[PDB]
């Protein structure tokens, strides 16, 4: 049962999921004195106005806000991409104290948490087919910097008491995922992987340069979730981040530089 504790955490994942030691694993440190420009890169296009959130679910690893991805209500295009990517869900990673918790780092700096907006390439018909392809998935990562409380985020945090344990779900309508974005969408990109098992090497990462905020009090709420199901031994989600993995000569590109 993979997790984040000392016996089942990231340093052990390679036993059941050997791709953990792969060529294109995520997250990574983004060293900003090593980032390259590429005139092929474009502005990020996030078309989220019509998005329809459905529900929030404690999956035993984090919690996911699920979207209707049966059509193009919430899509990602451009940036480094060459197709149309539908938003299926977003979730977060966070740490046990506010000084740590992001998966990506920027010149070794750790934010308090990181938002992952997970998308899949429509041409593959569904998420599972897409997850097996190098160009199949695209994840937008947004740092959460501890400081000012964030009203958009509060709406997510207000629902977490309804999904405290694994397998619980709650209705969650009308949440605009764009409300969790910075105003300007400058980004870094590189080829990588999912940051949880199965760790599949199918993700084009788009990591936004500008964090959104979170308060220290808000951060407490993330840590109240339970990894386990009702009636099982409790183990709170105090931390659920994978550390930086080796870049292995992949190119990190930046837009606009
Ligand atoms: Zn994630």
Image (tube, grey):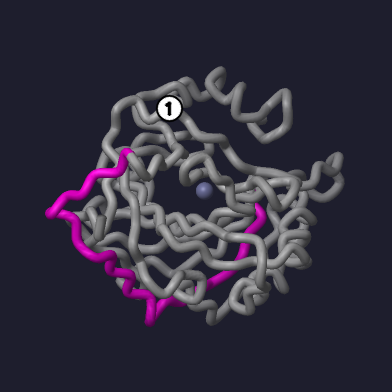
- Residue 238 visible: yes
176 vs 235, left or right, is left
Q: Residue at 53% across / 81% down in the picture?
A: 174
Q: How dense is the environment of label 1, judged by Cα within 10 Å: few (below 14), some, or many (20 and up)? A: some
Q: What is the span of residues highlighted in magenta in the rendered image?
A: 34-59
The answer to if 36 sits in the magenta stretch is yes
Q: Position of residue 172 (x, y in %)?
A: 61, 74
74 to 81, vertically: above or below: below
Secondary structure of the residue carrying tag 1 is: loop
Q: Which residue is mark 1?
A: 246
In the picture, the quarter occupied by the N terminus is top right
Q: Write the residue at 33% across / 62% down.
A: 186
Q: Position of residue 180 (x, y in %)?
A: 51, 70
Report whether 69 appears left or right of 159.
Answer: left
* Residue 168: x %, y % from top left: 71, 58
Identify which residue is drawn at 76% across, 44% down: 228
């Amino acid at each position: 049962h993979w997790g984040y504790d000392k016996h089942n955490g990231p340093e052990h994942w390679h036993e059941d999921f050997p791709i953990a030691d792969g060529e294109r694993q995520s997250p990574v440190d983004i060293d900003t004195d090593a980032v390259d420009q590429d005139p092929a890169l474009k502005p990020l296009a996030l078309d989220y106005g019509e998005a329809t959130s459905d529900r929030m679910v404690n999956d035993g690893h984090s919690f996911n806000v699920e979207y209707d991805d049966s059509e193009d209500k919430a899509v990602l295009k451009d940036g480094p991409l060459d197709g149309t990517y539908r938003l299926v869900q977003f979730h977060f990673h966070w740490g046990s104290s506010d000084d740590q918790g992001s998966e990506h780092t920027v010149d070794r700096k750790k934010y308090a948490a990181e938002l992952h907006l997970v998308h899949w390439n429509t041409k593959y018909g569904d998420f599972g087919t897409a997850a097996q392809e190098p160009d199949g998935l695209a994840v937008v990562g947004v740092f959460l910097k501890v400081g000012d409380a964030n009203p958009a985020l509060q709406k997510v945090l207000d629902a977490l008491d309804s999904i405290k344990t694994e397998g619980k779900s709650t209705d969650f309508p009308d949440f605009d995922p764009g409300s969790l974005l910075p105003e300007v969408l400058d980004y870094w990109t590189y080829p990588g992987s999912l940051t949880t098992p199965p760790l599949l090497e199918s993700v084009t990462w788009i990591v936004l340069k500008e964090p959104i905020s979170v308060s220290s009090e808000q951060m407490l709420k993330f840590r109240t979730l339970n990894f386990n199901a009702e009636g099982e031994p409790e183990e709170l989600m105090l931390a659920n981040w994978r550390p930086a993995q080796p870049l292995k000569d992949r190119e990190v590109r930046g837009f606009p530089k």
